[PDB]
Length: 119
Ligand SMILES: *[C@@H]1O[C@H](CO)[C@@H](O)[C@H](O)[C@H]1NC(C)=O
Ligand SMILES: [Mg+2]
Image (spheres, rainbow, N blue to C red):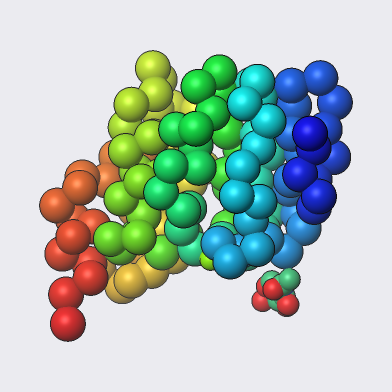
């Protein structure tokens, strides 16, 4: 079942470049998905569990989103930190908050993200 905003072929789900946000992302994706394209949306973080509910995912394309590296990014960060190679994710960059702006997502630590939600 291909989520409404996206185009699917095989086990590729193309949801790129569609103005998606956390609020508007599909709540689930075909459980057999192996490649998910989210490049070039409006995402600042990913809902908890979205990528972990995709147990066959090989690669996710996540670049060109305005990622905010705070505590809402703890789930994406965990997923990235668990990948077998982080180099394919080196185009993922934090735009905010100022203390993490310019950092690459795959090398963030969890504690940094907790700290980035300070009052
Ligand atoms: C996505 O962000 C762009 C760039 O700021 C904005 O113009 C556009 O309205 C947003 N699209 C949606 C669907 O929110
Ligand atoms: Mg968002």
